[PDB]
Amino acid sequence: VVCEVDPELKETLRKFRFRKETNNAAIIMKVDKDRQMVVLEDELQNISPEELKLELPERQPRFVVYSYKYVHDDGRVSYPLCFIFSSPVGCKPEQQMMYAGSKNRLVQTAELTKVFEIRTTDDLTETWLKEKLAFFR
């Protein structure tokens, strides 16, 4: 069963993509099993990678869209929009797979091309993120 993206979430994501703010911000999303929908859990502003990490459940999956201010060594700035599938190894397989099966639809909805996955929340570090993003540099 593939979850639909909640229409309200699609709107949240659309507005977020085109935000004109230049701080780091995140949208965290979860599955509503009963509705078979991906829904908004939290929208957070001025959130660093470590703070984001600390928001994520350690043993349940989440989807994240993270708008990160990437400061190049010379001081140029980019604002990549990242998808992070947090799929901790301690989650039940059924729950992992429920999220995994809905990931692509969500990514497509959000029109995201930078799609990452972590298998423990500990792996969400700024270093990891920057290295991931540098592939698109």
Image (spheres, helix red, strand yellow):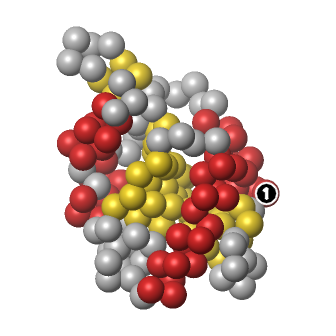
Position above or below: 1 against 81: below
Q: Left or right of 38: which side holds 134?
A: left
Q: Relative to the observer, which residue lies in front, 11 or 84? A: 84
Q: Relative to the observer, which residue lies in front, 109 or 135? A: 135
Question: Is residue 74 among the parts visible in the rendering?
Answer: yes
Position above or below: 4 against 112: below
Question: Is residue 126 among the parts visible in the rendering?
Answer: no
x, y percent for residue 42? 54, 59
Quarter of the image that includes the C terminus: top left
Position above or below: 43 against 98: above
Residue at the image point whose x is 52% and y is 28% from the top: 21
Quadrant in the rendering for residue 32: bottom right
Q: Left or right of 96: which side holds 123?
A: left
Residue at the image point whose x is 64% and y is 42% from the top: 111
Q: Amino acid at mark 1?
A: Pro
Quarter of the image that includes the N terminus: bottom right
Quadrant in the rendering for residue 19: top right
x, y percent for residue 131? 26, 38
